[PDB]
Image (cartoon, chains in turn purple, yellow):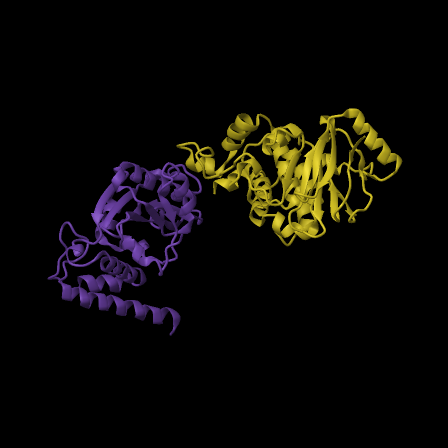
Length: 237
Length: 300
C-alpha cells in the first residue's frame, strides 16, 4: 500500500527499496516566438532514483534528444521514466534488485507497473508523503552534470556523502529531506546558509560541505528556521 | 413454439423467463411456460419469496431437448431436468395445456428486445463458460464467482469467462509498453479476436451473456466481465467498422433494458465516462450515448 507518516521507518529496514522521482525528467523554458506565440525549449533532465537506506543515487540523465519529434511529452516523460527504471533494475544483479519501488507521484504507478511486468514480485507503491526531491537540481554538482551532458548518461552518487559513518539512515534521510525542503522553499537563503563559511569546503567526491557534527546542528536549525519563516510569509500567519 | 412444464410449485417464488416474470404462490397450480420462441437461447430464473438473496436460473435452448422444472425439497430449489422419453413429454405438456395451467411467453410482436439482447449468444459457448457437461442447460446464480475473481475457490462452480487484464504480459508486447497500454488495438484484434474468440460474434456473445447474468442474477463478476469487454473495444484506436456499429446497438438495448433502480451497482462510472467521452470510440456510440444521457445523466 501507500507510504505515509505511519509506516515511515520501513524505509530504513533491510528490504532493498528505491524512491523514484520524475519531476525533473521533462524540463522546459517557456518563451515567446517572433510572431508572439509561446513555445517551449526543452533542457536536459534527470530521473532521481534513490536508495534511502544506503544513499546510493542512480541519476539517469535525460538528454533533450529523447524528445525529438515526439508528441505529448509530459505523458511520454512518465513512460520514459518507467523504461529507464526498469532497465536499471534489469542491469542489477538479482540480490541487488529492489523489493519495492516507491514513486513520488501517483501518475508513475501505471507506467512503472507496465514496465515492471517482468518483475511481478517487485511492489510498486505510491506515497502520501510530500517529499522534496524536485529540489535535487538545487544541488550544484547534480545540476552541473545534468546540464553539461551531451548524451544519455547514468551518473552514480552517494547523496549522503559520508554521513552514514557517523549517523543512521533514518537520521541521514531526515537531514537530506530537511536540506532539500529548505532548498525548495527558498533556494537563495538555503544556499547562502550552506556556503556562508568559506572554510568549510565540499570534497571533490561529495555533494555537501564537510561539516563537523556540531556544525550540522547549527545548519539544521538554520534550515528549520528558514522553513518556518517562509511558511509564515506564504500564509500570513 | 416450445414448452417448459413444471412438475409443481410448492414454494412461493417469483419466476422469470427472459425479461418477463410472474409471482407464483405456495402450491399454486402452476405447470409451466408455453409458446417459448424457438431460435434463441432462454433463461428461466427464480427468487423465493422467503430469500430475496440468491437469484438463480437456467440457460437453455429448446432445440437441444425437452426440459422441465421440478422443485427439490432436499436442496430447496427449482431444478431444471431433461426428459429423454419424447412421448412421455408430449404427453405431460398436452395434458397441462388442455388443463390450461400454463402461462404464455408474453412476446409483443413489435418487440425485438430478446433477440437484440441475445443476438450473438449461443448455447454451445454458454456451456464452455458454465462447465457441467452432463446437462444440456446451464445453472447460474447470484453468488458464483469467475475464474479471474478466483485467481485474486471451488472451480466446478466457476464462470469461465475469458480473462482480460490490461496490465498483463498477454496485453502488452515487450517494447510496446506505452503504445499497447494506451492503444489496446493489439490486445483486442490479435490476442482476443484473432487469437481466442476467433471472430467478433463469439466476443459479442460472451459480452451479452455476461451482461444478462449481471442483470438477472446480480452476478458481480459478470458485471466486471461485461465492463471489461466494453472497455477493451473503446480503448482500441483500430476497431472494425462493423464491430463499432454493432456494439452501439448491443449496448443500447442493454441500457434500455436495465432496471432504472439498479443503475448504481450495475454501471461502472469510470468505464462509461471513459468509453463515451475519453476513449478513441467516444464518437462511435451515438445511440448508446444518447440513451445514457437521457436516462442516467447522474452517473455521468
